[PDB]
Length: 121
Image (tube, rainbow, N blue to C red; front, side):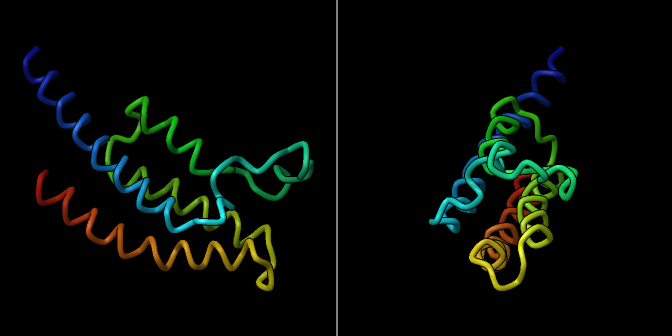
C-alpha cells in the first residue's frame, strides 16, 4: 500500500535523525569507554550484575536495521549504557565518571532531538 510506503519513509527519516543523534552522543565519549559490549571474557561475572547490557555498537546495529520505532526506544538503550555503568562501577572510577559526563552532555542533544522529532513529526 501507499500508506505502508509513507510509514516506511517516516521510519527512514527517523533513522536518519537518530543516526545523527547517535554520532553526537558518541562524540561525548572520546575515551571510547562505551563503544563496544563489555567483554564476558574479561568480565566473566558481568551478567550476574547487569541483566540488559548495552553499548554504542549494539545500538548502531539496531539503528541500521531500522529497529528504533520512536525516540523513546532509542533513549531507553542510551540510558542503559549509563545506568549499567553507574551500577557496576564505583563512584571513584574513571568508568563511573565517564558515564556521568556522557549523561550530562547527552542531555542537551536529546532535548533538541525530542523537539525535532515532534516538530517534523
